[PDB]
Amino acid sequence: PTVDDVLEQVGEFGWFQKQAFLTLCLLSAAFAPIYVGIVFLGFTPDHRCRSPGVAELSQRCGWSLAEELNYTVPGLGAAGEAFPRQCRRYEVDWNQSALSCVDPLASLAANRSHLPLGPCQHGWVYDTPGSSIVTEFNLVCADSWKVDLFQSCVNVGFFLGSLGVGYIADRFGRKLCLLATTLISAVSGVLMAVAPDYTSMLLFRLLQGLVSKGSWMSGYTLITEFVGSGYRRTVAILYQMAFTVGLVLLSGVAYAIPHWRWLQLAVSLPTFLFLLYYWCVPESPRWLLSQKRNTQAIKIMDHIAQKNGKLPPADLKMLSLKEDSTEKLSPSFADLFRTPQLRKHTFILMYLWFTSSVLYQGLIMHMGATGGNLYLDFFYSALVEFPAAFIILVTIDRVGRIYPLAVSNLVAGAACLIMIFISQDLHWLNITVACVGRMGITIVFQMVCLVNAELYPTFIRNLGVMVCSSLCDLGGIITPFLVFRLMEVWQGLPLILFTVVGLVAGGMTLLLPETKGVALPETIEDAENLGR
Ligand SMILES: *[C@@H]1O[C@H](CO)[C@@H](O[C@@H]2O[C@H](CO)[C@@H](O)[C@H](O)[C@H]2NC(C)=O)[C@H](O)[C@H]1NC(C)=O
Ligand SMILES: CN(C)CCOC(c1ccccc1)c1ccccc1
């Protein structure tokens, strides 16, 4: 009368499982905006120093946007690529000076560089009709570094939340966390749009980043526990796929409304609707059974059978774990580093997460020149993944869950290697090679997440995945400085490091035990002898 058997008797993947999966998918899409970053909320358009006198002259004679930029703004390429043109103003009086539009400023100085440069007061004038956070607070030239501060603070908040948010979810149940965390994320998101100053917005974003990771991973583990053993692959992969679909929808809606405040409010509000949809999904039976609350476990098991429409088995009265467990099974950080096998698995998974994150960031950094439209580039970036999801689904069932991950990691490493050695000059081959590498990285990410979730015991699963994911955020934070520093030593040093890291990760993946068609463990001692 183990949990898996009764779950099989009523139905592994029935009407109930599909219903829960639909709402969990809705939750998954809602996590994309927080993790996308500042791409659609902090895009920096072209900008020049506002000048009161230019407005009067703009209407006197025929003018064009291109023409105005050329012989009204200081020229670029002097003492920097574009530093002068960006945020320097000549300050030559353009008002009460009828010098003809043919020769507005040429006559005065007979030279452009030698003309006087003043402060870039009067705020700024931006190109895009929409408004971004940069445009809101003039974080352009003097405070340009504040954008880096904001993004780095968000990343640090994400790392800390990954390190900490797991324990509350594990100890107090998965439904409770998925409710409180998503509620906090929703109330903060709608609050950010009303943030008056720079500090308040940063604080609200930090809170949202601290909680969203916990929300998403709690949902993931809940659905994975609910689905039967055989169909774990399908549910997990399609959950990640729903996250990608949400990303695509985010790109579309972002193009729809450019204003950042309205975008944030519109993205945040539906999270309250999801919170309304909490009534459906109950607590995971496995967690309740491990916590020794068998009465609620059996009550839930009756409902799923009712919704499935299949008669429940008569043996539920004696439902319990395989062996008589202890009264208390409290999770703790200490328990995560006691069993040598568990310690080895944790180290390997942490290293795999770190390598995946660093290699992904490196690959996106070494890409080609960005396209004219940011939205189209982001849409293609998201679109590349769906074939990756299709490939992952087919191979997991038959090949296993180790060889695909190892080969994908090695493929990403080799893609970086070929990008380095073979001619990297602009060619049609480079874009396809980059897409291949991106596909490999996506496969690595999905496989790592699935295997890590499936490897740990049930009563600590969320905490383990959280800790092993924190290294992903750490690597994402640290890699840019590493790549900038290494470039100084030698021209192509970074790509050699990427290739060696990928090869080592692919080699190390082999030690991890396979998990093809094996019921996920529920006791630490049971997980110790998983390989044997
Ligand atoms: C950009 O601005 C410069 C201003 O110096 C333009 O140079 C002038 O070009 C016109 C013809 O288009 C000539 O009649 C002027 O004599 C040029 N100025 C000087 C000081 O010699 C330049 O053509 C502009 N380029 C574009 C693409 O707009
Ligand atoms: C779905 N594909 C695109 C990425 C899978 O990893 C996701 C990811 C990784 C860990 C936790 C959540 C989501 C990712 C998104 C953006 C940047 C880095 C990682």
Image (cartoon, helix red, strand yellow):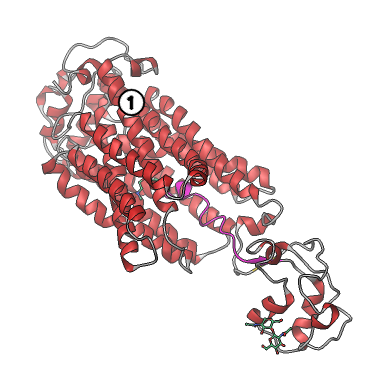
Point out residue 133 in the picture as x, y percentages from the top left corner: 62, 55
Point out residue 299 in the picture as x, y percentages from the top left corner: 24, 27
Residue 387 in the image: above or below residue 60 = above
Left or right of 266 on screen, residue 175 = left
Q: Nearer the viewer, residue 530 or 247?
A: 530
Point out residue 259 in the picture as x, y percentages from the top left corner: 58, 61
Which quarter shows the C terminus? top left
**Which residue position holds label 1?**
347
How many marks on residues? 1
Q: Nearer the viewer, residue 188 or 494?
A: 494
| Amino acid under disc 1 | Phe
Ligand 2 closer than 8 Å to label 1 CB: no
| Farthest residue, direction right | 96
Residue 345 in the image: above or below residue 224 = above
What residue is drawn where x is 23% and y is 22%? Answer: 522
What residue is drawn where x is 42% and y is 49%? Answer: 492
Q: Does residue 184 appear in the picture of this structure?
A: no
Q: Does residue 5 appear in the picture of this structure?
A: yes
Q: Tell me the magenta residue range.
A: 31-48
Query: Is residue 293 one of those drawn in magenta?
Result: no
Q: Nearer the viewer, residue 253 or 7?
A: 253
Helix, strand or loop for disc 1:
helix
Picture quadrant where residue 451 is located: top left
What residue is drawn where x is 27% and y is 9%? Answer: 326
Point out residue 258 in the picture as x, y percentages from the top left corner: 55, 63
What residue is drawn where x is 53% and y is 36%? Answer: 157
Picture quadrant where residue 227 is located: top left
- Ligand 1 lies in which image quarter? bottom right
